[PDB]
Amino acid sequence: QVQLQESGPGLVRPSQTLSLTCTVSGASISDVDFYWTWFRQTPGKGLEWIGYTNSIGNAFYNPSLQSRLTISIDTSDNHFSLRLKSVTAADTAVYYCARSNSNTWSREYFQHWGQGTLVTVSS
Amino acid sequence: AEYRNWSKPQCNITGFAPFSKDNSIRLSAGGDIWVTREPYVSCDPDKCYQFALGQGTTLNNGHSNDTVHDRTPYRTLLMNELGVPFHLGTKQVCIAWSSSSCHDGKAWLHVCVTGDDENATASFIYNGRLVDSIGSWSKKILRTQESECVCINGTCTVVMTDGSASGKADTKILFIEEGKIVHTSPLSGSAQHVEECSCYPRYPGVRCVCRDNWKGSNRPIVDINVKDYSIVSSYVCSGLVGDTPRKNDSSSSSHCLDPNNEEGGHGVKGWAFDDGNDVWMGRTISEKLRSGYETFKVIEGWSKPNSKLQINRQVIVDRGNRSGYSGIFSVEGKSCINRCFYVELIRGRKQETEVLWTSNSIVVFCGTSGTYGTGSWPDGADINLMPI
Amino acid sequence: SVLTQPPSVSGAPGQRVSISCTGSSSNIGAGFDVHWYQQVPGTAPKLLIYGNSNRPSGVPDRFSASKSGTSASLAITGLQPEDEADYYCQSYDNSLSVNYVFGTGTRVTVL
Ligand SMILES: *[C@@H]1O[C@H](CO)[C@@H](O[C@@H]2O[C@H](CO)[C@@H](O[C@@H]3O[C@H](CO)[C@@H](O)[C@H](O[C@H]4O[C@H](CO)[C@@H](O)[C@H](O)[C@@H]4O[C@H]4O[C@H](CO)[C@@H](O)[C@H](O)[C@@H]4O)[C@@H]3O)[C@H](O)[C@H]2NC(C)=O)[C@H](O)[C@H]1NC(C)=O
Ligand SMILES: *[C@@H]1O[C@H](CO)[C@@H](O)[C@H](O)[C@H]1NC(C)=O
Ligand SMILES: *[C@@H]1O[C@H](CO)[C@@H](O)[C@H](O)[C@H]1NC(C)=O
Ligand SMILES: *[C@@H]1O[C@H](CO)[C@@H](O)[C@H](O)[C@H]1NC(C)=O
């Protein structure tokens, strides 16, 4: 079974670079048939899709945040990472790493999720 | 054989190295070379091929006179291996004044549009035989990518436009399996005019940086998923727009979702591809005309709107030499997909009135992860030594 | 953009409730599949329905989904305890690029 484990700093200063890593166990991320997804849930709102990627590196990002993030892959260490630039008070949320069902776009549902890491942007 | 999957990561690109050059116009002055326009390059799993819409005549011919017309019944799609000039032994694979060819790893597929302007026929020729055909759904000039299409796992996607070249046109993405049209998805997204797309495989999707002939000097992007047949579209985020005519580098703009409405009344066929978050894009050096050609990387040019921070600029054709349609094609390497591009070097009418013909020669550059030098590779033909 | 849902939907044990997701032209109304996620607060979301009704595995038969036009509904028949969570409708949005829009989040409070 696919197991996802988010790991990253819990506190990032404003205008710094948020960097999270999701370690995958029980499955290989080097097979390009799934999208390795990142989500975030701000406390006052619902879930927000952050970005896509597969083992090949063809990533899709949320148009709202597209100017900032960079979702990377690492087929050797078997993990994928998220890198948000110039974080602010809107970037504090619980960040979930998930895997899509397949490599489609319109027919995508995210069955396997991580545990969720609270990333706080403050001073 | 086996179907091309394009399931390799994009190759590391630090720039583009010279790959091929046909010297078609130079050889035309003493040989029997086809009059050609709108060329493109597509590769087998083994070798790469040139393609061009021949004008039904050679240069040293009386019929080469007035060869600037885009659509004639005598236009055919020429085909030979890359480097071999379009001589009299060239194979005309179909009748077409608009074309697109991809190799799915098993056989060649040619999408050929011919016929009347208002009642054009698009013939789909797979494995050397006609398999399907469609008519003009808008009763205007039905056209296609004029470049290589992309087949992923045997499903080839071609972008077909039909309608006004200066207004709202109906663009449909056709999904073709062994020559048979298995799906036809209308263009969806924020791109308002899509024409002459430079498509490249971005597995599991296909990314097409097209030409906006209506309002935008920024090239529209068409993302096509070959699995669910879903289309999304936007515009290239870089503030260095790659479509001529355009404003100068200081005043140009792009915001990833709307045409910039800056000298967008016309356009040229061009290419762009994303190196992660950066964009590798080629454009003519001259803002107003198709004179010269340069390629560069814009840092964060695929994600950050109005990004003008460019690097790794290469002068493909010097400023004082004519260029034309550019486009992209992909080569499957040992472990990584290499992005290569070509530049059409148009010579003759209407810019050069010394001769009566309009023809071109191609120059091809392949992306490299190593180092490179400089240089300019124009057509090099002296128009005064050429037959009138 | 996001899809809209009622802020809260209550229901006694035994009876049934409905959660109404409302889409748009580049949304549920474009024929894209609607997926429903159940998230107990403080924990990770759990996929409940895909294909607008395809309860994957280990999901009680209480939950049912139906899509119509630009709207989708999640029906919980039974309102048993342990169904007190936030339910989000997810759908594909293609107005700008590859995007996935979630519902505002309905809080099912079993009185
Ligand atoms: C765009 O292209 C499409 C596809 O090519 C065109 O659709 C085709 O259009 C043609 C022409 O109309 C049509 O062929 C006709 O079919 C009719 C029956 O469906 C036939 O009756 C007709 O034959 C008569 O007309 C011919 C001239 O067109 C004559 O040469 C022929 O001898 C016949 O003439 C006799 O009969 C008529 C009527 O009885 C009589 O008045 C005459 O005096 C004479 O006695 C044609 O065969 C195709 O069937 C269409 N195909 C499809 C798939 O639709 C479309 O028209 C094009 N549009 C434009 C704007 O260019
Ligand atoms: C070339 O074509 C034009 C128009 O088609 C014609 O007027 C002319 O006589 C032709 N020949 C030459 C030598 O220009
Ligand atoms: C390619 O298509 C075939 C059916 O034609 C399918 O069985 C196979 O899974 C596809 N391959 C991939 C990688 O999607
Ligand atoms: C290019 O931008 C505008 C075009 O209208 C012009 O005013 C300007 O002088 C040109 N050059 C530069 C360097 O901006």
Image: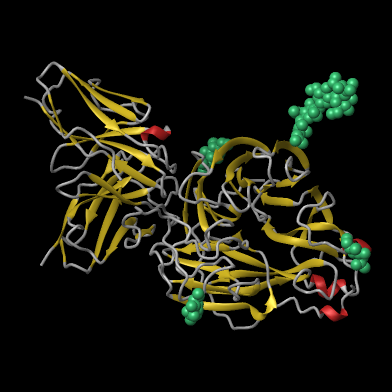
Left/right placement of residue A6 relative to residue C28 reads: left
Q: Nearer the viewer, residue B49 or B220?
A: B220
Task: Give how far across and how far down residue B257 sits, in percent.
Answer: 43, 55
The answer to whether residue B124 is visible is no
Task: Give how far across and how far down residue B174 sits, in percent.
Answer: 60, 41
Tell me the residue at 35%/58% (across/down).
Answer: A66
Left/right placement of residue B135 relative to residue B72 reads: left
Vertical relation: C76 (above or below) B83: above
Vertical relation: B352 (above or below) B195: below
Vertical relation: B184 (above or below) B379: above
Color scheme of the displayed model: secondary structure
Vertical relation: C55 (above or below) B335: above
Task: Give how far across and how far down residue B195 sits, in percent.
Answer: 60, 53
Tell me the residue at 69%/51% (across/down).
Answer: B101
Task: Give how far across and how far down residue B4 sits, in percent.
Answer: 60, 49
Screen quadrant of the C terminus of chain B: bottom right
Instruction: Pick out the residue farthest to the top.
Output: C14
Instruction: Pick out the residue farthest to the bottom.
Output: B374
Indicate the quadrant where residue A3 lies. Answer: top left
Left/right placement of residue B322 relative to residue B382 reads: left
